[PDB]
Each structure stands twice: as structure tokens, then as C-alpha cells.
Amino acid sequence: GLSDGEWQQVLNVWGKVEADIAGHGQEVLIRLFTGHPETLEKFDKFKHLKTEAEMKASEDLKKHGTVVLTALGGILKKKGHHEAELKPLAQSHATKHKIPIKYLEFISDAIIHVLHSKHPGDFGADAQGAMTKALELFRNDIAAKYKELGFQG
Ligand code: HEM
Image (cartoon, rainbow, N blue to C red; front, side, top):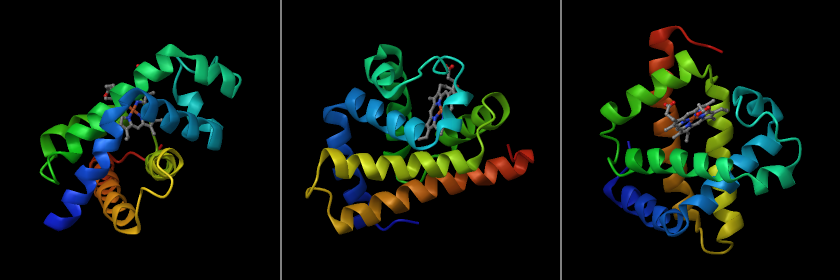
């Protein structure tokens, strides 16, 4: 898992997100969708977004960004003790949303990108390391639930 020091770094980085949850959430989803257009197709409510301009102008995309990062933030604040928070998310994403674990990898990478993009020079190597570990733990615990369900895609 993560050390106490690493968790402190994660939650310190997260303070950046919490100052503008909607903006971070929007940029994370836009990074995901533009980098990996197939991911948009999992969202019936975002499929109509034909351009990045349309994505940026979508209030509902911003809203969903807030939902996503709020959920992730609740999980991170548990510092690994997140079974109750994570299980339902893993299960909805496998069974209802049909989200391959690959897409969770994509969004994890998108979060790292967005943190650097929004805070260039202020997302240090230690912070990137700690946040990466936290996102890997998140993804890996989801992956375990996916295997339980026999879910691939
Ligand atoms: C940081 C990782 C993610 C978090 C924390 C997250 C969180 C959430 C939450 C809280 C919801 C609403 C409740 C629910 O249905 O369980 C949701 C819905 C959904 N998620 Fe995710 N999600 C993540 C990654 C992804 C990815 C990578 C995709 C697709 C590429 C995805 C696809 C969806 C879809 C299609 C819905 C239903 C949206 C709707 O039409 O309302 N999620 N997600």
C-alpha cells in the first residue's frame, strides 16, 4: 500500500482538485474523451459531443466531472480503507456501464496529465509518485472486483 507520508502527499495534491472540482473534473473527462474517443461511446449522454468545443461548453459534462472526482476524492480520503466506497463503483462500472479496466487506466493517466497541466511546476516528483500509487491502488482494487464478476469488457 501507500506509506503515511505518501497518503499525506496524495491528500495534499487533492487540495488542488478541491479548490476547483468542476474544472479539474471537466479537464479530466475531456482529456479522456479526446485521447480515447471510444470512451465517449460508453456515455450515451456525451455521445452527441462531436467536438472538444462542445465538450468544453457542456454543463452536464462539468457536472459529471464533479460527480466523478467527488467519488474519487471520497475514496482517496479513506487512505486505502475504501472497500465500502469502491465495491459499488466497481460493480456499477462493470455490470451497468461496461467499462473495461483499460478505460480506468486511461482516466488515471488523464488525472496525472491534468494535474501537471493545471499546476505546471507545482506537481512535484514525490507528489506524482504518491498520486500514481493511489490511482493504481484504486484501479487494482476495482480490477479485483472485475475478476470476481468475470468482467472484461
Ligand atoms: C476515477 C474513475 C471513475 C470514477 C470515480 C467514476 C465515478 C462514477 C460515478 C460516481 C458515477 C455515478 C454513479 C454510478 O453509476 O456508479 C459514474 C457513472 C458512470 N461512469 Fe464512471 N467513474 C470513473 C471512471 C469511468 C470511466 C473511465 C468511464 C468510461 C470510460 C465511466 C463511465 C461511466 C458511465 C457511462 C456512467 C453513467 C453515466 C450516466 O449516464 O449518468 N466511468 N461514474
